[PDB]
Image (tube, rainbow, N blue to C red):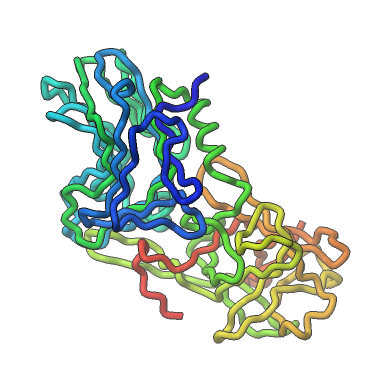
Length: 411
């Protein structure tokens, strides 16, 4: 029915409450806003990297039985140092006199704490490993949603799906703060930050459909995403992940038409001992997406955009293409000199893939210059070489370099 008792959004260069229920929003001097998507808010580990919301006194939580929910998106940079072991730090604080709620983070953790006014406590915790080949969660945008039913449970969801629920029914009067404080509080890692967006507060327990809808709407699947969940962009180099076989990367053997793109391995590993062990992400030839069909004056790659794909080899760009009249449904792809592409099939439709696990999947439907489908770019074995093909595993992700991952890129 109703919307949200707080609905926190960047609009005409002000962060404001669309619910109009806040006395005011108070932004620190070292809060940073992402230029392309200005709802994305970065908070560093400094004192003036903070936002304060002051609630109206009507909407302050002080109750035995009232239900309430919070949602927001967050991107949490990989934890690099040992200093981040065994250090819980608050990021969203609504406590007073030791009563209220807070969101807090630890190593591999997002935590929701409730405390009542008799020092009774409950935590619910989403736990995620950094000892993992590919993580859905490390340094990628995730949807957090936390619901509280005073009769039974407090529940935490990630990306729509229920992670963990704990009893809170033995907690009495919880009296939360007049103000919500967005700020890294008690973090010992000096270089820590977080990205955050779309904070909402609700005066009910959100049900599981409400949450999925919230997840869907706020995803903006209108726009394609890179691996981290930021907007996919033109004229930006990406490293390529093939989701079917994640331990390989794109290589080229030669350029021109007798050349071909393929998948080889291993991608290898990036490490710090006891802290993380993940697959290398900056492997292989970089792709740059080029405008063909869009008349849009930004650099944002939207669903069903029709594009050229360039391929960087020795810091020169070549056109991804094929001759579609080669025999067999599998059309091998090659990197071509951009002048000499001619009327080879080169146009790609960019298309986001809906489903339910890992976010930010893009497919790439190759077309000839009649705009007829050749097919989705994947790969196929030819005498155990996994050459890239358009054909009737074709789920890909595009990975730009990002401070939150911390890998040193060789090429």
